[PDB]
């Protein structure tokens, strides 16, 4: 018979977890960049 | 078998609390949202060019009603009144009498297109595939009484859309 | 066939609008988890009860 | 095979036409009366009667599941043909 | 005791909300429905049916 | 999938993901709109013997 | 949401009010190649929840 | 009598009243109220419109499906009138203009069009013809409106001998040009005496003239129940409105006293009770707001 | 003549201006409102036609009645229609707004919204697809395009 | 349809028409049944 | 009877029968009937005057703990003198079970309101009034909830027709939405679909 | 024949409640006329209230009149707060419908309705 069935090997894996990338610098480096920009502007 | 959403204890050490203070003093997550929207600006929009392009449809689509014919000119309906008995909205009115050659044919077949919920029970209760729901959906009118189809209008619709209705039935009838 | 699939039940902790928002988002993730199981475990056979 | 009433109105296949004294004809003024010009009785009248060499014949309208329910027609009467109840096709025994 | 005695006949016509035209000018027929002569079954004649008289039905000018 | 590599890199940087692997717009990977005819199976009561309805 | 409306109409014929699930099973079987499109949709859907 | 014109139902929206009426000038004020009263009985109405169809849109919900048939017509084209009136058993004429334009003057509106409609209806076998004239229509009057209206009334009478000619005095209503004209001027005070008549009683009298077969060939005169001086009427209008586009012909018309015609039958002979101005002036002029009643004569 | 041509071109200009900047006021009653929002989705995108999304009822041109109008709701609809500036148009979408549909014989359902407001375009379906409602909006634009207001004003 | 033409029929319209709403060629509903109750025609001769 | 027949749940049937005997033994003052259906549903038909204690017992006994009020319904059966049957559906999350409590009233007898037991009923039984005219005594705020404001009559009674007695339309003379007696363009076609042959011998009633 | 009362043990308390309801409606009517901007007078509204009260004045069962007083109180609270519109207040005044025939002859002329 011919029916709509999944393939014999099964379908591939499907991701479902939450994925936030965790990008970017730390707080210390961000604050250091801010004070560096301030010091350059003041000079 | 259960998970605890929003039961996280944040760290109280100096590094994490300085990261949090930098986040609420320099607006990190607002920049994240801005970056999301800016990245979504440079994607190709999914907008099609109607009416020059049409949305995809399946041959099971239920649109405008039509009355079919046999491939000899004889109309398929034999006035069995199954469609008007199964119609949930009572949109179908059928009156019948024997014609001059003695066949069982209808004399009145009205479908109230303002009552019909477009459910396809009539086309699945028909034993001869006389009434069908065609693929047409661009048939909006300007007057209420134009949406009150009689037998002549449905026969004209069948003669107009047979070349597509027959192909849809041929492609679909093995699933029925 | 809900007893043959595996999924998680998100449980809130404060009863506010934010926890109900997070529960509704997590239910979309769990619905994907059941969908992947239903595709790989679809059996052949008929579609209606054979009592005509 | 349409015909035209003396008031200028087309008669449908069901024989319906509006009388000259009927006011409802005012619904057709400025518009048109929609009729179907393909009459089913006229179109089935042109179909030739099929000659078969058996006592009974089976009709399903052609196409198998795309036609009507299958029926069995007796052809013992030599005076008249055996007409199908659904499709209107007629058969005749050649003996 | 929290119970009172009312010996008058029951009359709820003021509470049903039906207009009086369909109250005093209607005749209600209470009957056991007759068996359909095209069938031999008798399951439709087991309960009493109450219905009303039939008023005018006319023809729509449009359809 | 018609974007330039510079625009693709800009989108990947600003979004944070690799968007080219998971494109929401459909393409040639989808099924054909016409399909071969099927042959549907029958139920368990499609039998000629030992198939009385009272049981 | 529009892509899942195609799944309803490809299996029942109507985009929203399917009248598909009936007492005794379902009205019509899945058309050929429908579950391939469901797998293709749900494979990329975890990214769409993350953007929201 | 055809079978489709026999009355049926209970006089509701979807019933059949057996009236096929062609209302000329139904897009105005009196025509609007007449079509509204005709459609609630399930009567078939044919509306010929000269203007844009959008201006007829408010006439659409006044009846059931197919009970109102909109169609085009021209005042100088007899073929359009023949197309409009050939399937109806009553024709009502309400065509009028307070002012004359470049294309149409008073004579064309009040004489040529009513005579053409009457002649076409007579040659099409129409049973009832109603023509709405004015009460003060006199041939020797000092305004072209009243002179041409009297001439057109005479021409309608000779062309259609069984025509019901109705002469309202001065109609006040929600969309009128009588109380709204006085309220919007923010001309003077004379010794004019007038009897304003409510629009609903005019519509009821027209409907009763349709129903009653005695009214054929008569000439009614619809007047109100009270006679007011013009100064007192203007003072009452300003008092009820809390107030401390025109031409010379309108000024001459409002200075003409309403003549007394006891010989002509009125609203009381058609079973219609006349509504006084005091009960309806507040609902007419509530929209002008941001009371001692006037004395009669 | 000169004046007929001038008023014809002016009528064409105002017709294009009115029909190319339609601002709709939807009525979020029932299923058909969900299909309306699916028409406003990025695939079909009413906004590219100049038809903005969720305009205020105090500045809107066309009212789209999408859903079932009940007896408890009709005076509010009439009030909203009466407080809308001319020129105004009404589009009935779905079977409920056209003729009652499934609930035609109900005790608390107005059998068609044409009993309350005058309707220009009737969109059939239950629900009519987003393409069908877009086609009805385009047909309303064609109906506005062939307006002849200034020609009637000059001819009268 | 250039690759797979549709099946030819004698009643299929050779001239497709678009939507005719708002035009003189629109569709007007009517009853397709005939008269139900026949009325008695009085004789054309007097009883004299 | 394997493929197409619904399997039975005998252990649930035994447990529900035991709990029904338990409840009918604890409260003999108010309960009148205890039944278990073939698909394992427990119905406890009680006197109306015990509508307040019994529910409270089911809300508070450590062996019942029916803390959830799933539904509240009224059923109109005109052949009885007490034509209104009032149905409470209770859900117990602790024991994962459902119960049904049924009382009977006519049009004029009031009912003690179960707001003090279940707060959700504060809307539910109110809807019952708006659909049936069953008055609920000691209700905090009893009024209509679904019908129109000037609506006369209770629609879900079986002597109320499908279309009502009035219908709305806009009138331009009074500039208002007005109500008029109902006149349908198409009559609702009543279908007599009941076959004259008996279908279920197990539900056959004894004759007279 | 012993029944559970709703509010009143006999007819006297029911008549007292009827009196209170009529007093409240008579006090309410001018506020309804002024607030809703109706075109009717205070006399017409009070005559309408008296018309309903006399129309519904043939009952003798305490529970029925108790329920009638309850429903009248519900209508009174729907009128006290602005929940009814102008249309719901004017439902009691049937202005749009034609006056039905009363004698035998007019009903014979218009149709088959008895
Ligand atoms: N004060 C009053 O109201 C009184 C009025 N009358 C008479 O009653 C009738 C109706 O009055 P009223 O409603 O107030 O006036 P309107 O001006 O409001 O109504 C006149 C109607 O006739 C149409 N019309 C006018 N001129 C022409 C024309 N040349 N060709 C075709 N149609 C035309 C108008 O349509 P459109 O302009 O849109 O084309 C409109 O529908 C008139 O005959 C008037 O003389 C009598 C007594 C008192
Ligand atoms: S689709 Fe359904 S509602 Fe429409 S005519 Fe057919 S059976 Fe009736
Ligand atoms: S079900 Fe088919 S054959 Fe029967 S009456 Fe309807 S259209 Fe005709
Ligand atoms: S027409 Fe159909 S889809 Fe639209 S509101 Fe009515 S029931 Fe819902
Ligand atoms: Zn055959």
Image (cartoon, coloured by chain):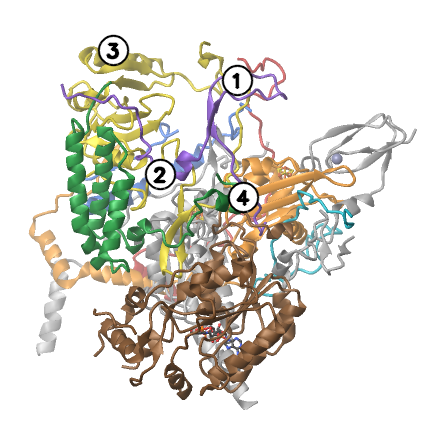
Chain colours: B orange, C blue, E purple, F red, H brown, J cyan, K yellow, L green
Badge 4: residue crowd in 10 Å (few <14, some 14–19, many ≥20): some
Callout 1 and callout 2 share a chain? no
Look at the picture and state if H294 lies above or below C26.
Answer: below
Q: Is residue I44 visible?
A: no
Q: Name the one closer to the observer, L29 or B142.
A: L29
What's the CA distance linking mark 2 and mark 4? Answer: 43 Å
Badge 2 element = helix
Q: Give the residue number, with chain letter if any, for mark 1.
A: E43
Q: Nearer the viewer, residue I156 or H116?
A: H116
Q: Nearest to the eye among marks 1 and 2: give it.
A: 1
Q: Which mark is residue C33?
A: 2
The residue shown at (18%, 49%) is: L26
Most extreme residue toward the bottom is I2
**Dot 2, crowdedness within 10 Å: few (<14), some or many (≥20)?**
many
Same chain shared by disc 3 and disc 2: no
Measured as percent of width and height from the top left, residue D36 is found at 70, 53
Q: Are marks 4 and 1 on the same chain?
A: no
What is the spatial separation of the Cα atoms under label 1 and label 2, in whole angstroms? 52 Å
- Real-space Cα distance between discs 3 and 2? 44 Å
The residue under label 3 is: K21
Residue at figure coordinates x 58%, y 80% from the top left: H112
Q: Which residue is mark 4?
A: B91
Disc 4 sits on a residue from what chain?
B
Marks 3 and 4 belong to one chain: no
């Amino acid at each position: 018979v011919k029916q709509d069935m999944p393939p014999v090997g099964g379908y591939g894996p499907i991701d479902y977890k939450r994925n936030l990338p965790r990008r970017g610098l730390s707080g210390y480096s961000m604050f250091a960049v801010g004070i560096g920009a301030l010091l350059f502007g003041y000079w | 078998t259960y998970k605890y959403v929003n039961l996280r204890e944040p760290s109280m050490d100096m590094k994490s609390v300085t990261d949090r203070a930098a986040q609420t003093l320099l607006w990190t997550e607002l920049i994240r949202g801005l970056g999301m929207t800016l990245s979504y600006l440079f994607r190709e929009p999914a907008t099609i060019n109607y009416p020059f392009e049409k949305g995809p449809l399946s041959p099971r689509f239920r649109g405008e009603h039509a009355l079919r014919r046999y491939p000899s000119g004889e109309e398929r309906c034999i006035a069995c009144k199954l469609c008007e008995a199964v119609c949930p909205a009572q949109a179908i009115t059928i009156e019948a009498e024997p014609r001059a050659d003695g066949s069982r044919r209808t004399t009145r077949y009205d479908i109230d297109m303002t009552k019909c919920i477009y459910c396809g029970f009539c086309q699945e209760a028909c034993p001869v595939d006389a009434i069908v729901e065609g693929p047409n959906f661009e048939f909006s009118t300007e007057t209420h009484e134009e949406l009150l189809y009689n037998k002549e209008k449905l026969l004209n619709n069948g003669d107009k859309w047979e070349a597509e209705i027959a192909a849809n039935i041929q492609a679909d009838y093995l699933y029925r | 066939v809900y007893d043959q699939v595996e999924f998680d039940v998100p449980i809130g902790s404060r009863g506010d609008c934010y926890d109900r928002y997070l529960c509704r988002v997590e239910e979309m993730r769990q619905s994907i988890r059941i969908i992947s199981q239903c595709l790989n475990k679809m059996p052949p056979g008929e579609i209606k009860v054979d009592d005509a | 095979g349409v015909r035209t009433s003396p008031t200028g109105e087309k008669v449908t296949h069901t024989g319906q036409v509006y009388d000259d004294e009927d006011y409802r004809r005012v619904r057709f003024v400025g518009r048109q009366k929609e009729v179907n010009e393909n009459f089913a009785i006229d179109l089935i009248a042109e179909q030739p009667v099929s000659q078969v060499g058996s006592r009974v014949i089976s009709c399903d309208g052609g196409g198998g599941a795309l036609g009507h329910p299958r029926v069995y027609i007796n052809l013992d009467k030599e005076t008249k043909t055996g007409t199908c109840g659904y499709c209107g096709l007629q058969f005749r025994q050649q003996h | 005791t929290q119970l009172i005695t009312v010996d008058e006949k029951l009359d709820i016509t003021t509470l049903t909300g039906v207009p009086e035209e369909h109250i005093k000018t209607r005749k209600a027929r209470i009957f056991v429905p007759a068996r359909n002569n095209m069938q031999s079954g008798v399951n439709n004649t087991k309960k009493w049916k109450m219905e009303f008289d039939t008023r005018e039905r006319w023809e729509n000018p449009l359809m | 999938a018609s974007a330039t590599r510079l625009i693709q890199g800009l989108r990947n940087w600003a979004s944070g993901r690799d968007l080219q692997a998971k494109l929401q717009l459909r393409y040639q990977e989808i099924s054909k709109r016409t399909q071969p005819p099927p042959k549907l199976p029958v139920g368990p009561s499609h039998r000629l013997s030992n198939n009385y309805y009272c049981a | 949401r529009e892509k899942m409306f195609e799944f309803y109409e490809r299996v029942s014929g109507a985009r929203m009010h399917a009248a598909y699930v009936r007492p005794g099973g379902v009205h019509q079987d899945l058309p050929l190649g429908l579950m391939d499109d469901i797998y293709e949709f749900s494979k990329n859907f975890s990214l769409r929840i993350d953007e929201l | 009598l055809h079978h489709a014109v026999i009355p049926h139902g209970k006089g509701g929206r979807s019933s059949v009243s057996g009236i096929v009426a062609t209302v000329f000038g139904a897009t105005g004020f009196l025509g609007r109220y007449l079509v509204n009263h005709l459609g609630r009985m399930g009567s078939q109405v044919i509306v010929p419109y000269r203007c844009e169809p959008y201006d007829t849109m408010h006439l659409r919900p006044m009846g059931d499906l197919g009970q109102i048939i909109f169609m085009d017509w021209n005042g100088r084209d007899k073929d359009s009138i023949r197309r409009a009136v050939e399937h109806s058993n009553v024709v009502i004429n309400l065509v009028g203009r307070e002012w004359e334009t470049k294309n149409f003057d008073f004579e064309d509106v009040f004489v040529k069009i009513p005579q053409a409609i009457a002649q076409v209806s007579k040659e099409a076998g129409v049973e009832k013809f109603i023509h709405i004239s004015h009460l003060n229509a006199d041939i020797k009057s000092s305004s072209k409106y009243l002179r041409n209206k009297a001439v057109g009334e005479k021409e309608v009478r000779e062309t259609f001998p069984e025509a019901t000619i109705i002469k309202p005095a001065d109609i006040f209503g929600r969309e009128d040009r009588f109380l709204n004209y006085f309220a919007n001027i923010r001309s003077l005070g004379k010794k004019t005496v007038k009897q304003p008549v409510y629009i609903v009683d005019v519509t009821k009298g027209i409907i009763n003239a349709i129903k009653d077969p005695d009214a054929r060939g008569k000439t009614f005169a619809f007047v109100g129940p009270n006679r007011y001086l013009l100064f007192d009427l203007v003072q009452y209008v300003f008092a009820v409105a809390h107030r401390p586009w025109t031409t010379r012909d309108k000024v001459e018309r409002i200075h003409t006293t309403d003549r007394t015609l006891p010989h002509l039958p009125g609203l009381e002979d058609l079973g219609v009770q006349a509504t006084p101005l005091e009960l309806k002036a507040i609902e007419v002029l509530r929209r002008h707001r941001t009371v001692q009643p006037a004395k009669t004569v | 003549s000169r004046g007929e041509y001038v008023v014809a071109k002016l009528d064409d200009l105002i017709n294009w201006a009115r029909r190319s900047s339609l601002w709709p006021m939807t009525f979020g009653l029932a299923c058909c409102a969900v299909e309306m929002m699916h028409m406003a989705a990025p695939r079909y995108d009413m906004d590219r036609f100049g038809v903005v999304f969720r305009a205020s009822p105090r500045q809107s041109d066309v009212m789209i009645v999408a859903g079932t109008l009940t007896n408890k709701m009709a005076p509010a609809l009439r009030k909203v229609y009466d407080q809308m500036p001319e020129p105004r148009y009404v589009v009935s979408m779905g079977s409920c707004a056209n003729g009652g549909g499934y609930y035609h014989y109900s005790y608390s359902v107005v059998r068609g919204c044409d009993r309350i407001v005058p309707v220009d375009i009737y969109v059939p379906g239950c629900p009519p697809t987003a393409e069908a409602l877009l086609y009805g909006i385009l047909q309303l634009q064609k109906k506005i395009k062939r307006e002849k207001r200034l020609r009637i004003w000059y001819r009268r | 349809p250039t690759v797979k033409p549709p099946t030819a029929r004698k009643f299929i319209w050779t001239n497709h028409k678009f939507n005719l709403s708002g035009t003189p060629q629109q569709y007007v509903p009517y009853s397709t049944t005939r008269k139900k109750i026949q009325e008695w025609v009085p004789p054309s001769t007097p009883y004299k | 009877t394997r493929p197409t027949v619904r399997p039975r749940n005998d252990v649930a049937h035994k447990q529900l029968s035991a709990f029904g005997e338990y409840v009918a033994e604890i409260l003999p003052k108010y309960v009148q009937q205890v039944q278990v259906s073939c698909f394992s549903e427990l119905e406890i038909c009680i006197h109306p005057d015990g509508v307040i204690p019994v529910l409270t017992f089911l809300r508070d006994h450590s062996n019942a703990q029916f803390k959830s009020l799933a539904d509240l319904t009224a059923v109109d059966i005109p052949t009885r003198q007490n034509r209104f049957e009032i149905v409470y559906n209770l859900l117990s999350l602790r024991f994962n079970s459902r119960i049904r409590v049924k009382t009977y009233t006519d049009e004029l007898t009031p009912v003690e309101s179960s707001v003090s037991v279940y707060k959700a009923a504060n809307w539910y039984e109110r809807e019952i009034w708006d659909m049936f005219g069953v008055f609920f005594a000691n209700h905090p705020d009893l009024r209509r909830i679904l019908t129109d404001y000037g609506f006369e009559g209770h629609p879900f009674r079986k002597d109320f027709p499908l279309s009502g007695y009035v219908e709305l339309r806009y009138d331009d003379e009074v500039k208002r939405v007005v109500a008029e007696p109902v006149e349908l363009a198409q009559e609702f076609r009543k279908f007599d679909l009941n076959s004259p042959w008996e279908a279920f011998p197990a539900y056959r009633q004894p004759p007279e | 024949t012993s029944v559970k009362p709703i509010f009143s043990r006999d007819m006297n308390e029911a008549k007292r409640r009827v009196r209170e309801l009529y007093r409240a409606w008579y006090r309410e009517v001018p506020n309804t006329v002024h607030l809703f901007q109706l075109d009717i007078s205070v006399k017409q509204g009070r005559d309408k209230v008296r018309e309903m009260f006399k129309k519904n004045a043939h009952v003798t069962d305490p529970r029925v009149v108790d329920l009638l007083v309850i429903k009248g109180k519900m209508e009174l609270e729907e009128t006290i707060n602005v929940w009814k519109q102008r249309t719901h207040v004017m439902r009691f005044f049937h202005e749009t419908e034609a006056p039905r025939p009363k004698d035998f002859l007019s009903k014979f002329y218009v149709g088959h309705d008895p």
